[PDB]
Image (cartoon, rainbow over all chains, first blue to last red; front, side, top):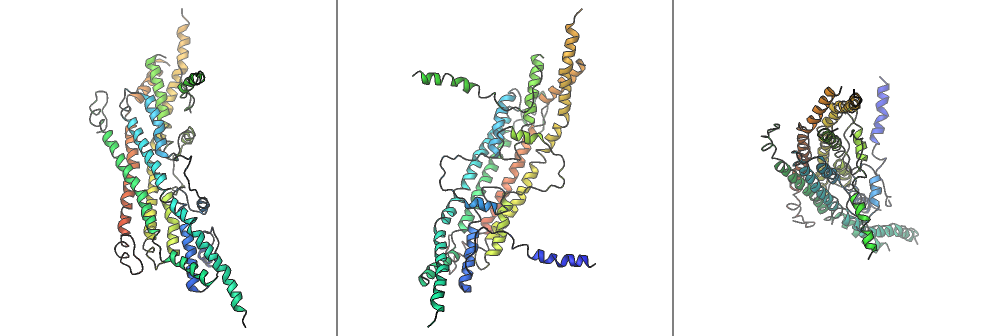
Length: 243
Length: 243
């Protein structure tokens, strides 16, 4: 009865320390009073959070910092680059050829090109889905990464550089005021004036959302375009079908 | 003016013969009169069409016979194998940790876990999407591949085997009737009695379709759960926001 005791005694420490082992892709700022160290740590969480949503919409598997390495490389122009081909275009690309190869004297000939044009028009919607996820969700946050975030990192880097310079200036008894003011104004801008990312998430969920209803209400029309075999080919003299 | 003539003269043959170069993964049956050779060729198109829809729903890129090689390997049991993790589970898996790491004294604390639980409940819907595409669309057609299609290929193989045997029996002048009857009944079963795949496509489009409306009408609720900042935090004394 002592093994299952000692088995839970050194496993509680392993279960308690299972958090601080991963989820790191950048450095850490210099350890300032709690009014400024809390703003600097909140800036570090704001940096890791603003640079950890854009890894999520392009690939479909993002549980790891490999998607953050995929996010750290960035692209501004879309020139000489087409859309990525999706599942519904390839779900109808063969079926067009299968419908013109199978046979026209059969009720599948009024049926396979209906599903083929259905999949080929969900193909343009999924071509739109990769564009509305990359133009209003990937683009302005990336331009804010290479915009004022370099200015914020520059002002806090010169803050942490010249803080030790004024430590050298004040500790010998007998560039930090203006730099700390611009840095603290940037930190209070990215904490208090945070009306930049509520709209980004609230428009990203609408940009994902307004494709699902369109392709659903277009796939509802396939039962109307395909409803002739429970009404006209149901009464066929060759075979009966499902009503 | 003769170069652009000859350039469009040898290129018409290349544009006319751009079809018969690919799209082949099995063999061809033996070349029988047109009432039986047309049924045998229709059986070959029925075989390539029935064995070329199941390659399309699992992977998202199927323009080539590599998806047909992925389709030729088949799996019956789902034992000791979980669901594949999708995009919305991984779209909220970090955001739960980001919400409990960022800060609770801010209106994002009433906002990030809302989007996180939204993405985590689209995660179960995309966990359902890989199951309704693999259980009612991949499973019974695969059981029909290793079911009566082996019987159809066996009866037509013995047809093409003993047809030359009765050619040997009849051409020397001075097992094919019953085999040809069972084979022709199987070919007329897979041509005329074709009420097996209208329901499969008509239920595959409903199985894809009834996820889109559910996740759309669940993402419409995020504007209601997130509508408190255009009504209560809009009148906040720190900052105004968007209405």
